[PDB]
Amino acid sequence: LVSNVIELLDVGKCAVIKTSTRQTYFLPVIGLVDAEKLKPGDLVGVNKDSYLILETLPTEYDSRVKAMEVDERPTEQYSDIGGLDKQIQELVEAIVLPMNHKEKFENLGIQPPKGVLMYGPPGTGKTLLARACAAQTKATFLKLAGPQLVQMFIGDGAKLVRDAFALAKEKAPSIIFIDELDAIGDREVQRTMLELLNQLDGFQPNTQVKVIAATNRVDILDPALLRSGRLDRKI
Amino acid sequence: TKGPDAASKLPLVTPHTQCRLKLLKLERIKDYLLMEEEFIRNQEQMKPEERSKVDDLRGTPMSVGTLEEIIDDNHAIVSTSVGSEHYVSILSFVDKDLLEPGCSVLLNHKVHAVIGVLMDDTDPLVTVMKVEKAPQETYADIGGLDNQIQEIKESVELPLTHPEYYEEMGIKPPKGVILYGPPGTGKTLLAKAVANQTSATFLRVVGSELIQKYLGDGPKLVRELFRVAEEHAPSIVFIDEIDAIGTKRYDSNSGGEREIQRTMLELLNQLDGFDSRGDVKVIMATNRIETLDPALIRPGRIDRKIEFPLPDEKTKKRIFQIHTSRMTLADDVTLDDLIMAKDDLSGADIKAICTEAGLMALRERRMKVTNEDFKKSKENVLYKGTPEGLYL
Amino acid sequence: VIMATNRIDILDSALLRPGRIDRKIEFPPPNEEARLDILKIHSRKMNLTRGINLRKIAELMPGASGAEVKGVCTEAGMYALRERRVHVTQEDFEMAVAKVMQKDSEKNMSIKKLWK
Amino acid sequence: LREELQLLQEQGSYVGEVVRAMDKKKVLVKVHPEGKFVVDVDKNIDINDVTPNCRVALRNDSYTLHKILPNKVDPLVSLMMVEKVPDSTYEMIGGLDKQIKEIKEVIELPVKHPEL
Amino acid sequence: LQSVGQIVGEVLKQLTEEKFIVKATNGPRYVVGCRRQLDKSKLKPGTRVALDMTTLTIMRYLPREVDPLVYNMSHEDPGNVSYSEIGGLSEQIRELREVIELPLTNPELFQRVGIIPPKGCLLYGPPGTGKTLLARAVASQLDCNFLKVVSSSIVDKYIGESARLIREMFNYARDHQPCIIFMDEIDAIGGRRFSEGTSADREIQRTLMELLNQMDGFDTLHRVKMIMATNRPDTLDPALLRP
Amino acid sequence: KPIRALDEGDIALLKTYGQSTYSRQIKQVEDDIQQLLKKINELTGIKESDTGLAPPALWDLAADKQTLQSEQPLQVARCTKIINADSEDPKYIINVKQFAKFVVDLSDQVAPTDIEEGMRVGVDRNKYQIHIPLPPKIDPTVTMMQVEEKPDVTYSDVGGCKEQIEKLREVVETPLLHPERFVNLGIEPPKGVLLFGPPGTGKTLCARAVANRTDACFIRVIGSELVQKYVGEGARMVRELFEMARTKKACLIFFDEIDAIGGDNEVQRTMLELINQLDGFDPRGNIKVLMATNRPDTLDPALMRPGRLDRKIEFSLPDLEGRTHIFKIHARSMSVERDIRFELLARLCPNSTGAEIRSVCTEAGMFAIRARRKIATEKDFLEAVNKVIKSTPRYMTYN
Amino acid sequence: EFLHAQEEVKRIQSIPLVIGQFLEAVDQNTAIVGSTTGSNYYVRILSTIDRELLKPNASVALHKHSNALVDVLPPEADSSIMMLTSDQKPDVMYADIGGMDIQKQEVREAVELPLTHFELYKQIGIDPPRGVLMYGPPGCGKTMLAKAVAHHTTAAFIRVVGSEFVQKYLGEGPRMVRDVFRLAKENAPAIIFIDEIDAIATKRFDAQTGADREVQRILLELLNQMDGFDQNVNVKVIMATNRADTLDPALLRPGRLDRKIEFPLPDRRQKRLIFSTITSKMNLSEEVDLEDYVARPDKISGADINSICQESGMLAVRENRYIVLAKDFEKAYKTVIKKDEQEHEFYK
Ligand SMILES: Nc1ncnc2c1ncn2[C@@H]1O[C@H](COP(=O)(O)OP(=O)(O)OP(=O)(O)O)[C@@H](O)[C@H]1O
Ligand SMILES: Nc1ncnc2c1ncn2[C@@H]1O[C@H](COP(=O)(O)OP(=O)(O)O)[C@@H](O)[C@H]1O
Ligand SMILES: Nc1ncnc2c1ncn2[C@@H]1O[C@H](COP(=O)(O)OP(=O)(O)O)[C@@H](O)[C@H]1O
Ligand SMILES: Nc1ncnc2c1ncn2[C@@H]1O[C@H](COP(=O)(O)OP(=O)(O)O)[C@@H](O)[C@H]1O
Ligand SMILES: Nc1ncnc2c1ncn2[C@@H]1O[C@H](COP(=O)(O)OP(=O)(O)O)[C@@H](O)[C@H]1O
Ligand SMILES: [Mg+2]
Ligand SMILES: [Mg+2]
């Protein structure tokens, strides 16, 4: 019987679970399976009667991320993008060149760029170059929207952005992609960009997943985002 | 399908003036009722294998479920009232041709195989939602609204009576009609009058009644209501206060709002479900017409829109004549000064004015309402514009 | 059915409609005679002193609701209690009226003199 | 004591609303939340007394109609009955004489003498 | 294999020395006893507890359930940043070190001196001035529980949720003493309460009112020191700004 | 003047005083009438339901007893992730309706091949092992999926959308009728079009007209259906309908009211399944999809991306010639005079949708019925357009 | 045999038992109970159960395997809102609150004296105040006086904050108000303290959205619970606010808030009393002009005086000397009451 592990508690670890029969139970011992990873939310196959965790199952869909189509094969070879030679050279040298020469980066004792940024008039190929980079790097693509996030009530901060980043890191040849500028009463966007800065700044050491943060204009710029780390590589 | 089970509709006594003729008619009705009770009781008194074995096979108790699919002639997908659904068998004695997705199959308590079907399942809510005693109000009790009554009779009565004109002209009968106007204009009274004069099943619904706490109970209730209406054809469904659920459609976040939207989308779907040629019509009333969804009132769903304006001077005097038709007024009461006063008097306001005038008459130890009593009553019942002097 | 509210004007017209609500009774703040009646009702259990003129106390409460009259009685009783007595004098009622009906006025005379 | 101990060991009976008596042996009743069952009536209860929408009792798990219970009124609303009358009389109301008469002309007069 | 797991619920009342009213989560409530060897004196009302599935007796106690946003906000690694990585803040870092850590290291010094330890302080300044860094370093030095929350991220569309989140934050802080709640951008929740205002304006006032009562309110705070960072100290509410 | 409460003497006098001599008898008779009616309704009662017992010629009672004893009942569940069975992990997540979710093995009867994600699995009641897949067997003649082969409406019936009908003709005919032209022009045939315009403009009718002209069967799918009770296996719905379309000859897929679907877990399953049936299915097929909703933006952004729905046809409110053509089309099916000025009626209803026009014609018919006339006159149409359209100011300052 | 049978009847009342609501009595020995398991059962009432405690919706204990109405519980044992336990009681005494003699007296006359000397009120023949409003500038002693009242009370103290009432789910705020007042009623003479009452009790207006309507519903439920149809007995309610003028007039009337006690900023003598009562636990001040510090005209609340003393202690710790003198006390005074303006000169 499948259950959703609510949390793990220390006693030497105990976990409380919510079985799929809308019942919340406590476990002094964690079943017949290991108890180290045991993510707080990992679905577990618990006993039908004694309710002990026999074994753990693969993860589940988190709604919007399933709705957030991967389109894993973008089918580009840089022959689709034309006229942006300097731009794609910059993109390569900003994302994949540090990806393969991260050793030369830690020799310098500095961290690789954790995210590229571009800006320009609409329809100039910003998304096409993103898809091209995803193809040449065989990295998972996520087409996060910019105007869509401003709506959807208060909550499109650390509930979707974090959702977008989080489970991308296991099928992780990955390149998550911000799109048309967004607004980079007026308090929801403030929360959105606070989530952005304090989640992108909380990035991965090897940076196995990168962010590309295409926009539509250079008029509206947040220094907390356009700084180093978050969005410094600008094309 | 079984025909329309209309209301009781005891015959109307015409005099109503507390005279001998009223006594004669009422005594005649009482006489017929007595000879009816005598016959029913005496015929109750006079004159007195496989069925028992099939009852044994059914077992005890037998649960009631709703059929949803039929894979083969010996297997189906029934759903218990809880919400769970099972792949169950159909035993031989169950009459197959009655099995139709949406019926009420009788299920064995253990191994819920279909052992019978229930023609009448109607739950207590949809059962009380059906009119049994016709309201005493009648078109004679409605003052004014000649155009409104004419439109409602063209909409829910003319197709019911001789309808040959509708297909002679080639136009479809108006599927559903909605009444709107300021509160107290006659929207509910005009539905009472329809129920009193109808020859079809009348289903009164509060609108807010359809919403139910448990998940899936709202759409199920709406589906059962309209299934009863169709199965009870011809029938009329009066969903009063449609704005209780008819408000503007907006994106839902909470589960309850999702269930409300589900209930209304079910109601809209089932309104689309039956053909206009069908003898089931819907009647809806509201005060806030502007707050309704601009999809329930689509021309393809509810073509007619009967307006109920505040009564004019002649309609006001007609309503006053109707509501003072049972009073012992004097010869001094003009009743014209009141309908003169440019106010927003409605049918409800006029009825309350009459009641208050009666109470003033009682306050004077007299049973003959005078003009002074009406004068004080009008001011007493009228509650609550432009400053005096601006507009001459 | 009986209903009560302090804001009738915000009530819906479909609910205020006659036939659903007839005889919308208004409860205005008591006048001087009614205030005196309320004072005599709420001072029935007190130990008043000979020479008490509740009419003057009622005249001292212009536009005071019945609840404020009961509060005046209660505060006069408390003024008696503080001095550890059981009887209540006219002065006690006067200070009770002053305390209960105390309200913040327009401190700025300039604002108050906007209107003639 | 021994009889009470004996009847305290039998399981409680579910309550339910009989929507209609289908037959002189079967009764279809909705029980919350098990669902709707067509139960039988035991030897005691006469079915002609089983009226639609009346609260009943069904046995342990055989679901046999064995008692007719008073009509269903949910506790959240049955609490609104004023079982303990409050101690406030018209003699303790100052002013509001006209208001009292007006409220009596709608609350008392109709119920007392509807003939008028 | 031998274990059977346990029902978990919250104690509601202590009927007597043995009979406890316990409500299971998303289920019914019972009157239950407790295990023979157990500290009954701590089983307060509202304490999450575990029930044996069969006999339905108080099996063992549980720490109060932590809110998921509170969980994610409390389980973020500060990064054990030392004090050397601040620079040019000597006077201010010394002051904040005093006000926060001195009550957390030698409370007897404050007890002797004659004062109650101060309950928290404010760091205001232009963005990028390292107030977040300074608080993060304080937390690492103290090696205590640290709730790093950002105001304007606890606000919610639902009417009563932001104040509830503040309540849960401070309840965790009290449960996990010693603790330092760093609320950044307090300028968001804290804002001179004013009348008029849209529903949102009022909702934020209600939240500020909770924060205020949750800091200096009937229930005194202990070993829970707060650090609040903002760029617009001038717009903060006087009641919040009050000592 | 203080009101005086009615004394008991006043109550007694007022009751009797002036009254009909018959009034007592009338009141008693009426009360007895009500009591008698209640008594009749009490003594009729007990109407026999007579449950669905077939005639005894069909009862094999022994066989029903044996099937009651033997045939186990299986609860119906919705399957989920296969959890990489591959004969090493033959387990699946199954959601047993409102009861719960479980992870269950197969049965000896079933095989792994016919069990995948998303179809209706009949699980047992002890071990909950999947014992028989139950495909929804939808083929829904009881609901939507119009499945109309040759709609009665034709090219003449649609009026006013001449530019619209021409764009539709191009996209869904020139590849369909002249594939060789697109092949020798080196371009994939138009994968589909999104017919967007204000509701009631007639886009559905224009699509059905071209369907009748193409002689390709017209499939209309509603969205509210699979938002309401028939949710979940909607992926299998579209799977089977696309499959039978492949079995069918040249077709015309049409999604109306698809805004409900586009605007999401089972819903998301529905559109990724149609992605599998549009991108995965070769774009050269004759099952051309005709997308149509008022909303031009609510459609999911991954849907109109190139290699998919390729163009958009913008329907607009009919013009004067369009309005008079619609009026003539709708009045052809009516008993009216031969000298009706339909141009006049088209003029009198500017910015009026086609549905408004059909409602105007219906109201004209009702107005003719009102005067009990078998033929509707121009005055009836004028009054109908006065009633429907507009739901001194324009006559006293304008002239 | 009677002893054995009585033992068996006592044993059936053992634990565990499922809680249920006594819906309605049918017979002398049977009843209808709605078990908390979500079902309604027709069960048998134990004879030993006292009957007049068996009121509708009263929480009763049912036998686990038979649902028999085994025993009845205290009327509001399963209350969602918790009271103030003995350990939760604050340690602030009336002595620690310097000054505000009139404020203390006016609170006590409504929250303390009626509970201990009700015979005085009965002799005078007046209703003791049931409800006091505690308003004034921030940090002038309101919540401290509430804490002190909770310390020096034999009542069942219920502490709530105004914002706590506002719930996410619709109709849960008024429900919480109803439950807290019902808990106070069913308990002994009780005190309800609602800090920051103006979070929910702002002046009613024409609400145009669901949230505002719900907040006004909470306020209306508070009003109808305080002075509604069914009056409360021995239930005193204390509410503190910073802005009394924004409170609804229906809340600010006698019978609901009989006394609106103002807590002004300390003046002269009050400042001296506050300084003395806060510096009592302080070390000796080596003869600093505390009376002159008091004499300085400054609009500072008691919280500011506590801050001045706290700052003095911090400075003394920082410079490592346990005995405060005028230097660090003066620096603390300047720091606390800074009142920095910098305002452009054209304004004044
Ligand atoms: N035209 C009329 N002639 C006579 N009486 C009328 C008329 N219109 C209204 N009334 C009186 O008004 C009373 C209330 O009217 P009704 O119930 O029809 O209102 P409604 O318009 O449906 O109101 P609401 O939408 O506010 O519920 C009726 O009982 C009837 O006595
Ligand atoms: N240099 C280019 N070469 C080829 N195609 C381009 C180029 N620039 C833009 N496009 C076309 O424009 C579209 C991408 O627009 P883009 O600017 O990426 O979207 P947005 O502005 O919405 O982010 C693609 O269809 C792509 O074929
Ligand atoms: N003394 C300092 N003042 C300001 N910034 C500093 C200091 N030392 C380091 N930093 C840099 O500033 C960043 C701190 O950001 P943060 O604390 O969020 O600033 P703020 O508190 O203004 O939001 C660190 O990433 C660090 O690289
Ligand atoms: N151009 C047109 N010619 C003839 N009838 C039309 C036209 N446009 C709309 N209609 C009428 O509209 C009605 C249905 O409209 P529909 O096609 O459902 O609107 P939508 O554009 O929303 O699909 C039909 O009765 C049809 O006769
Ligand atoms: N009269 C007083 N005597 C001593 N200390 C006081 C006095 N008034 C206020 N204080 C100090 O101020 C604080 C009171 O704050 P509080 O009463 O909660 O403010 P509010 O008025 O906002 O409730 C106490 O911690 C106390 O140290
Ligand atoms: Mg009505
Ligand atoms: Mg306070």
Image: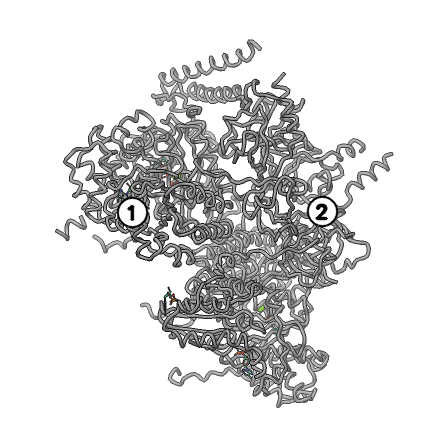
Is residue B346 toward the left or the right of residue E184 in the image?
Answer: left
Q: From this viewpoint, is residue B263 visible?
A: yes
- In the rendered view, tell whether residue B187 sits above or below residue E105: above
Residue at figure coordinates x 51%, y 68% from the top left: A195
Element assignment for label 1? loop
Is residue G106 toward the left or the right of residue B172 in the image?
Answer: right
Classify mark 1 as within 8 Å of ligand 4 or not, answering yes or no. yes
- In the rendered view, tell whether residue C25 sits above or below residue F30: below
Q: Position of residue D114 (x, y in %)?
A: 45, 30
- In the rendered view, tell whether residue B244 sits above or below residue E139: above
Classify mark 2 as within 8 Å of ligand 3 or not, answering yes or no. no
Type of residue at label 1?
A: Thr
Marks 1 and 2, Cα distance to the nearest angstrom? 60 Å
Asked whether E233 or F136 is in front, the reply is: F136
Asked where in the image residue B382 lies, by quadrant, the reply is top left
Q: Position of residue F261 (x, y in %)?
A: 43, 49
Say if labels 1 and 2 share a chain: no
Chain that bears disc 1: F
Q: Position of residue A197 (x, y in %)?
A: 51, 72
Image quarter where the C terminus of chain G lies is: bottom left
Chain that bears disc 2: A
Asked whether G332 or G34 is in front, the reply is: G34
Element assignment for label 2? loop
Q: From this viewpoint, is residue G309 visible?
A: no
Q: Which residue is mark 1?
A: F201
Please identify the residue farthest to the bottom as the structure is shown: G327
Image quarter where the N terminus of chain G lies is: top right
Q: Which residue is mark 2?
A: A49
Asked where in the image residue B349 lies, by quadrant, the reply is top left
- Please rate how many residues cluster around mark 1, counting C-alpha atoms within 10 Å: few if below 14, some from 14 to 19, many from 20: many
Q: Are marks 1 and 2 in contact (CB under 8 Å)?
A: no
Name the quarter showing ligand 3.
Answer: bottom right
